[PDB]
Length: 564
Ligand SMILES: CNC(=O)c1c(-c2ccc(F)cc2)oc2cc(N(CCO)S(C)(=O)=O)c(C3CC3)cc12
Ligand SMILES: C[C@@H](O)C[C@H]1OC[C@@H](C2CCCCC2)N(c2cc(C#CC(C)(C)C)sc2C(=O)O)C1=O
Image 1 (spheres, helix red, strand yellow):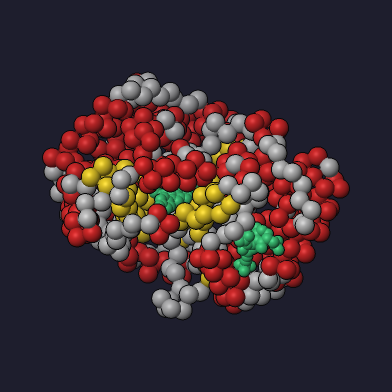
Image 2 (image 1 turned 180 degrees about the vertical axis):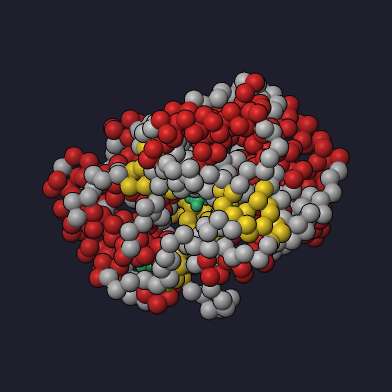
C-alpha cells in the first residue's frame, strides 16, 4: 500500500514562519556569516510529501518469523502498569500542542477538571470503540540549518503527524510504562537508548575491540517511518500484548493500534483533509519504541539471511549499527549486499548502500562518530562527536530569537567532551546567562528527543554523571576533529581560539566569585582557559541527581517531559 495518499489540500502553518537570522550583536559575536543560516517553512512541505510517498511491497521469511518468536518470548518477561491520569498529565511538556477541545498543556499539567474530564472520556472512547480512525494533524517542522551549495538545494521541511492532546495523554496512560521498560527486556544490550553518552561510547569501543577482526557498518533506511507497514505496526502490537498488562491497558493498546498507530486521516492547521497515512506516525508515543523494535527485528533477521558472523547490533529507533567478525574483504562486501537485499524485502531499503568499515572512528550513526583525546591525568579517552555546523547555526538562531524548547543546552549536555561544545557553546551561553542574571532559570531542552527542564547551574553535575570527570580536561584532540571544527569556524565566520579563551577566562572569574553552583561551573567547565589549572575532583552533589527516568526516547514528537 501507499505510505500516504494526498487530497491536494496544502500542509499549512499555524503561525508566521521566520526564515532568516535577525540583526543581533550577541548572535553576531558567535557567527558573522548570518546569511548562511536559514529555517525551513511549510512552503517546502510538498517537496517532503513527494520523498515520503511511495508503495511498500513487504515480503517476510523464516528468519523474520524466528526472530519475532524470540522477541515475543522475552516480552512475556515484562510487567507494565497503567499510569493514572495524574501521572500521564505530569509527563506532558509545558509547550505541548493545545487540544482542539478548549484546554492546553497548562490545563493538563495542573489537573484542571476540564482537561481531566476530557481525557477520561477519550479513555472510555478507546475502550468502547476499537475501529474508528482517530484524527491527526500534519504540520511542517521549522528547523534551522546552514546552506551547503555543494549538494545544491536547501533542505525541505520535515513533517510531523500527531493526534490531539487528549489522545496523547491516553497513549501515556496505556503505554508509557511499556515503552520505558519493554525494549531493554526484548533486545538487552542491543537497546541503544538506555545508555548515557559516556556508557554508549564505552560499549561501542569494548564491543569493537573484543572482536578478533572487526568489521562494522551503519545502515540508514531511506524514510524509515514511511517504510513501516500496517503489518509491522500489528507485529509491534503483538509484542506489547506479550507483556503482563491490566485488562484496560490491553483494550486501550488494541484500540490505539487499530485507530491511530496503523494509520488514519491527515488534517492541516486550517481543518482541511490533507489525505491518509498507512505508515508510522512521527508524533505518537510509540514512534521511538516501535521504530527500535521494528528496526531490530528486521536487522537481526537480515544478519541471519546474510550469514554475518557474530552480529552485535546497536539500535536507536531507525538508527542502526552492526559490528561483526570479518570473513575477509570480498566476503564482507558480499555479506553486506545480502544484508541490504534482506532489509529491502522486509521494507527497509537503504538511502545509501552500507559500506563495510574496518576503523571504528570512520563509522557515522545519529550524525555522530567516535573520536579520541587524553585527559588531565594523561589517560586515553574515547568520546562521541559530530560536525558542529547545525549545533552552532541553531545556537546563533536561539540567541537572536526566543525558542521555547532550545537545542544548545541539549547539545552541551550530549556533546560536553567535544572541542566545539567546550570552546564555543559553553563560553557563549554562560557569558549571556551571567550578564542577564539567568543562571538559575530552568530551560526546556531535548535529550534523545524527549523534553527536559534543566537549570544551567547543574551542568557540571550532569556532565560528570553522563560523561565522567575526564569531560572537563580533554586535550590532544585528533587532527580530523581539529580540522572539522576549524572548517566550521571558517565557514560560519566564528571567532578564533584566542577570542574564546579570553571570553572564557572572564566568564570563569565572574562565576567563581558568585560561589556555590556558579563557582562549580567556572571551576569545571572553564578549567581549560587558565594557565594555573585547579584540581578537578568528583563533585559531591553529582550523585544527588535523579537520572533513573532519563533517556526514554521521544523522537519525533518530543511529547515526554522530565524536570531535573
Ligand atoms: C546506533 N547509533 C548509536 O547508538 C549512536 C552513535 C554511533 C554508534 C556507532 C558508531 F560507530 C558511531 C556512532 O552515536 C550516537 C550518538 C547519540 N548522541 C547524540 C544524539 O543526538 S549522544 C552523543 O548523546 O550519545 C545517540 C543518542 C540517540 C541515543 C546515539 C548514537
Ligand atoms: C586554551 C588553549 O589555548 C590551550 C589548550 O587547551 C586545551 C584544548 C581545548 C581548548 C578549547 C576548549 C576544549 C579544550 N586545546 C586545543 C584547542 C584546539 C583547537 C582548535 C581550533 C579548531 C580552534 C584550531 S586542539 C586542542 C588540543 O588540546 O588538542 C588547547 O590548545
